[PDB]
Length: 104
Image 1 (cartoon, rainbow, N blue to C red):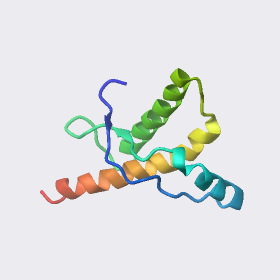
Image 2: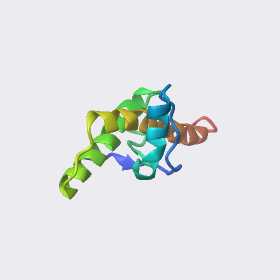
Image 3: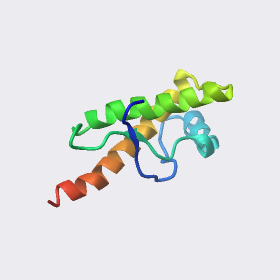
Image 4: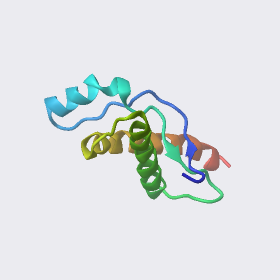
């Protein structure tokens, strides 16, 4: 890493995939997926969605490396599913933080 902070928590947000397999399949294993993100604070980094791009690409990698030291590895599939959640979780944190900045 190098200065990515953990965001707040909001359980494992439910995502749609257009297909009863992928949709239920996510659910079936949402009891192991991320409930917080890795982002960076302000006075150094900011944007609308780009402030989530790097964040998500970090939180995600972090749950892959963790498995490797445990003797496990997610795939690009379990990562592509995380990319949807971890994004919205990063945007939902960003908004809650932005409501201070905007309120200044």
